[PDB]
Amino acid sequence: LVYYEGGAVCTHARSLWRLEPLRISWSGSHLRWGQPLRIRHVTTGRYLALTEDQGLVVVDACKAHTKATSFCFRVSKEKLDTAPKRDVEGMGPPEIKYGESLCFVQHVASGLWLTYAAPDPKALRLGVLKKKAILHQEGHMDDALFLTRCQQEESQAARMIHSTAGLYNQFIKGLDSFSGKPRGSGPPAGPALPIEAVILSLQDLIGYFEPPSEELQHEEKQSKLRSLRNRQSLFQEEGMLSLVLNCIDRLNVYTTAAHFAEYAGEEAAESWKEIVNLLYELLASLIRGNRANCALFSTNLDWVVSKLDRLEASSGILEVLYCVLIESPEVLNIIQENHIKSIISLLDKHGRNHKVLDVLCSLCVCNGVAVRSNQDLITENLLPGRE
Amino acid sequence: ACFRMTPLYNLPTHRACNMFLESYKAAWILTEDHSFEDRMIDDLSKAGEQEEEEEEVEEKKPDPLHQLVLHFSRTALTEKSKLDEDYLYMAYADIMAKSCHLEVEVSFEEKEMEKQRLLYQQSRLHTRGAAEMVLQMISACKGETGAMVSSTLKLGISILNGGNAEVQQKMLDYLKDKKEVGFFQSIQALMQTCSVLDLNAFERQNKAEGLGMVNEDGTVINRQNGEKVMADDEFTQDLFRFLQLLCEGHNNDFQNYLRTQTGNTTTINIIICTVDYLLRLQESISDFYWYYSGKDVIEEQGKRNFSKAMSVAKQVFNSLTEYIQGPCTGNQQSLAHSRLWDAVVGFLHVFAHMMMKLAQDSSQIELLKELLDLQ
Amino acid sequence: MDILELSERLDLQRFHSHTLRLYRAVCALGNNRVAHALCSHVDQAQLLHALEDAHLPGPLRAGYYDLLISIHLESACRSRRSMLSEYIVPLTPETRAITLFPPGRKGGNARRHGLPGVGVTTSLRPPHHFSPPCFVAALPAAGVAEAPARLSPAIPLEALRDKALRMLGEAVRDGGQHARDPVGGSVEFQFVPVLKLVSTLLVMGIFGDEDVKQILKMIEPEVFTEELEEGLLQMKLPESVKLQMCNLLEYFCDQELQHRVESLAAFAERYVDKLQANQRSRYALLMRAFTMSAAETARRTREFRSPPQEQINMLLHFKDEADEEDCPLPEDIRQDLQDFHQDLLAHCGIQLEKKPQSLQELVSHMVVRWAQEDYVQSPELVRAMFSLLHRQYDGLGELLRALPRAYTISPSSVEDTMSLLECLGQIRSLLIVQMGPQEENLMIQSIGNIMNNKVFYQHPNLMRALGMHETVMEVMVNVLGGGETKEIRFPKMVTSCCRFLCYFCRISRQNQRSMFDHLSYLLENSGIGLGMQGSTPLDVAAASVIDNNELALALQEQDLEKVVSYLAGCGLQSCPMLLAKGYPDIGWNPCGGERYLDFLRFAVFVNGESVEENANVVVRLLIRKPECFGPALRGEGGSGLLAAIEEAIRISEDPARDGPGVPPEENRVHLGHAIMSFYAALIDLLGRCAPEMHLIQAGKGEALRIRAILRSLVPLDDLVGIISLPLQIPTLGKDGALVQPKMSASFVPDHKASMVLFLDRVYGIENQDFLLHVLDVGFLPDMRAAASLDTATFSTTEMALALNRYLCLAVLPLITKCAP
Amino acid sequence: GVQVETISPGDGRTFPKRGQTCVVHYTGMLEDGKKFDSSRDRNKPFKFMLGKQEVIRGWEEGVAQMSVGQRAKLTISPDYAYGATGHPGIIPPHATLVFDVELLKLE
């Protein structure tokens, strides 16, 4: 469903659309008034359409048959209907400007106008500032739309979000295909997992979210930090963090590579450790330095803590915990004695690793404010033993 | 209570000492003058005895003033939600600004000498990154009014006075290479936060000054707490003076850049923003005139509010004139298609009626002169 | 193994350094109990050994120095540094003896500067408190969060400072020797820890005059002589050591500023005595002026008819030499002030050679030389040097900005001021710790001790200069922001802070104005104060404007809009913690509505007269958001006010609709009582928004329009019907026990008093027939009931007292007005 | 719960009495052998008055059985000590404490 929404949505990836004219050659030419084109949602890959049942919706590519998904921009709502303009072989005459031209979106086949649905009262108390977008015969006087440019970084991020979401959803459903179906002495009996594609995508994303080097100069380092924060926020707002968590959980229901092979086969299980390590590294890259993303673990912290004893990705899980604790005081305010005892057991069972000490240090003070509960719990559960 | 009040010699020693401290700092320390800005800038502008090697070090590591400017630029470029208050930057910005001006038939020789002296004093700053620091701080304030942005604007005016073409070129080049929208977003927000005349606040102030209240420890004679009518008049004046100085000398490139920013992802029309503020100011002035139309003589508070509004209007008119002079045909067309005509119609109405009203009593001749020069 | 083997076992070295980091973290920011626990793991002998150990690896040396500071010095140093920014100077003979320059013969305008940090300082600073670390002491019978807060573990400070001085001298000599094996592996590791320790002890005030002289000799042996040894400032140190030197010089600059403030206070003490003696004499001979003068004696005695601040302003108004006629002081008295002004300017280095000869020139030259010798890469170091340089260049400006925090007190108030400073120190120390039960006990006891102090009430100017209301506001906004929507913890501390701020407002009008500067800042936090009962941020904001015409007039319209928006929200969605307790879900929140309405009442009514500027805005906002009027007075499909009151009475009489139906909760909320309380508050607010009779007879259009709108909102028949409703009267029966109504769950005379106020101010009584019609239905039965209740048994009952208040505040004055 | 073993004999006649300050040097160890307190690393004798219950029970009963100048080893049962709670961060719960006490002088 399509809505007119304001606020933080103006900087998110779900408000990005791609204008696709009904031709391949010179599809990048200047847009013209009355030129038929499709409108495609970048992150979801669905095309704006007018259906006989639900009206104005976004449909999949298999249902965009140029009659429901043909729109045009018109300078005014007057029923000109002069003649069908013939396309030229070139850039053509430049007509529609960014941020200055007021455009009216009209469905070509039906002639309806894109407008809001005039939300019913008693819905304002709910805080619903969204207005449903509908196609109407008349519309309103304020139906004109401004076309605003999108940054290359944001466009690339949105397309990457689309592709990554598709790939990881395919991987998740492949994992769920044999969730409780042992293969025995036979094939897993299902489509092959996209192991190589998932590994390459994880590596590409890890390199995409790499923090800027400390040897860079101050101005470009700050610019790169700003871009990294924006990309992390976009990916988080599109649910990629939750998608990574789902992949991690579904791979984590298996204790080891042989246990995974008992269900998916040896050829798939020989990449299980690599994939889980890459998933933890990607999660750390997504949340590193971003307080908004780190604050999401203030509700699910046992999810991270309970995985500290896992032997395949101990360093990655510890790094995720460190990144969470460094940024979010909300997570510090929920730390409990069992969490601290688990972190101490990490020392006891993995040896003298100074990163655990750093994690414990971060548990005490954040942004110049001390947590007496954490300090006392660490002092009580670590010092008197003298071991 | 005047006839029964307590003499000073009966007060407790500590109370009298506190009163003496207040009086002494008010009348003896504040009144003291000590010009150290020029001496500080001269001391910081010297590189100390590092010229006995003259090797390929010609990178020429910054002198102390340059390092201070770079430090302030660094703290301005840090990514933060808000621009925090910084008394050190405040004080050093005031020092740099006061270092640059240092100012009945002046002859041409000493006129040009004053011009070259001002040019050199401005060069001492804009050869060390002050012009970029000003823009970075304006962008970092993100359109939040405050003493930090006021100090930044005063420094910008101080280094742009007289229409310094070199500083204008440096600022324009920096803006065009950075292609950041934060600068003009902050400028637009600041211009939208500028206030105009408020009749409700004027009436509240009239009632407050009519009540005549005093304090506990002693008795205050009509305390002069902050004016709430056009409180930020000096800030509005310095903002529009900065915008005018960006275009001073008929800088066609900057006049066009204020109207449209080609390289940026989004564009803000500062000319139209100025027209909008002029409309709001004109409406406020018309409301004030309607308030005082019935009364025969305007009192002192109304006269002073009228004078400060007129000064703000003078600055806005000068800014628009600097936008369009040269001429800048794009700015001329943009103004011709704006509500400038409506603002001028309202101003003509106010001008005619205020001249006719003020001409009937000689106690308002100064206000009439101010109105005439505004016309 | 030997700990010195960690110079080659790098993994163990890193792990142990991070262990020391964790030791510092667990006891960080005033965790004295954990510091006492840590004293059992790294003991004082180990710490003192590690300080002097020359073969320790650099990380371990720095970690042990910082561990000693954290365990034993961090809390005291922080508490002292917080107090070092204020100058409360007692008027004692030691203070009187203070002079800007030492007694000398260099020059009359200015002698030679004394050594910074050396001399007599009398500004009040609370002493340090330490507890001996002992782990055989009996376990306290007091439970947690009730035992007194632990103090920092004690370590011999004299021995520590002697060791630190000796170590610093040895380090200076070693750096002069230019050895190839510096202690700790580098010059940074050799110097930074020792300088940190010395700076901490200097701030704490451990060092005496001789120790300070020695430190000055190490810093610069040539500049700091009173009348290879190369000093620290000429040894070409790295940037960390430069930053530590900047800290030391910042301490000495602070000492110079404090000396200037104290000298100014001492001169104030002497000059005030001289001025008072001269003024008494002048008044004495002025009382005989009629024998040789005329009516112009008023000009001479105008001094004695002017506030003492203005008297002293005029007495000091002789600086520019064009004001030598109005000032009546003799030239001999004027000369003392002029000489002190000249010597103060000289001491600030205004006006009156490779050797700097003074701290100001030394620091300025050092900073400029450091900046022009290399491109400094540490932003912290750069900010430090430039702050230091600016302080040297503007000494008069530094003093001028420091004076507002300077205050002089009588020597008899020193102990009470010290106690207040201690309590304020405990309050400030808890700005850097997450909020808890022990911290709540400390907040409550500190606020109580402050409020029981006579200084807090005798010196509102001092309590304002100390930033105490800001600190209390900061802690209370912290606790409110914690859990700002679901549940507020530590309500006892929240109401302690709120009551403290209300009393702070009540002390003086200047305090009230300072609290008024945060009016919107309180209102924005007042949205979630509904669940809390007692003193609230809304109560503080109301107390910050009550009975103050200036603050009422200066009230911004945005604040009133916010309050009305909160009221409208209360009038549409039920109260959530009321819902969570099983109460029936009516479509509004009368309890919250009432407490917003009383704030509006305080905003629109001052000193018995209506503030029309606020009243018009409030009425306009209320009509623009009609849901503020309750489910009744809704217009379409809404019942009348009298019908609403009767429905509320029925609800009160019927349980399972008045309460949860599971005081029983000690603050039980009864829905019917809440409803008529809300409507009474609304009617009272509207009546107080009514224009004054003078504005009415003047024919002002705005006043007439507002009165017409109010009349349209509330009908006279409904007012009279509410006034005419019967009240439950305490009767006797069933062995003679008193059957008294529950005043918290029943119709009460205040609800009638609000209607009477509205009737008087809006409609008024103008005709005899209407006056008698009101009397014989609404007033006379209430008077008869009150007269009946004046018996031996019923006289002191709550209902009888309420009826007496209702008659003597609403009914009888109205009748007295309608007597003709 | 106090067990006193002599290390070096005292004078043998002077004994502490209620209301008399005992100046001692001690070294506290857990029964595992881990040191946790000692007044000699602070170079300051520890003073306490018998009967005021300023110290744990084991010290009050243990030192009372000592003479001036005697060095003795006290093994304190946990219930004659910090017990189930235990000094947090210092002494674990249910800890038997071993002390090396020397009664320097009575004052």
Image (spheres, coloured by chain):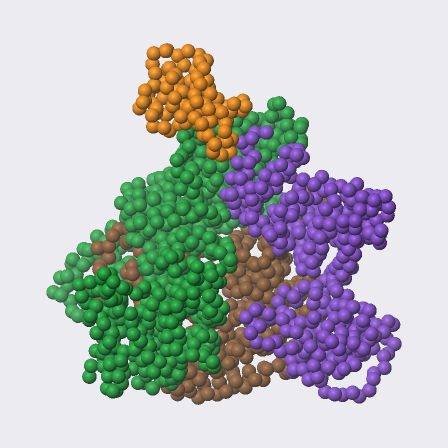
Q: Which chain is green?
A: C
- Picture quadrant of residue C174: top right
Q: Residue C92 placed where, x, y %?
A: 29, 43
Give the quadrant of the C terminus of chain C.
bottom left
Question: In what quadrant of the picture does the N terminus of chain C appear?
Answer: top right
Residue in view at x 49 percent, y 48 percent: C434
Colour for chain D in the figure: orange
Spot occupied by residue C46 in the image (x, y as percentages of width and height): 52, 27
Pinpoint residue B325: horizontal percent, then vertical percent: 63, 77
Q: Chain A is shown in which shade? A: purple
Q: For chain B, give the colour.
A: brown
Q: Is residue C725 visible?
A: yes
Tell me which residue sits at (71%, 55%) in the image: A243
User: Relative to residue C302, is residue C17 depicted above or below?
Assistant: above
Is B339 left, or right, of C518 in this rendering? right
Q: Which of C50/A292 is in front?
A: A292
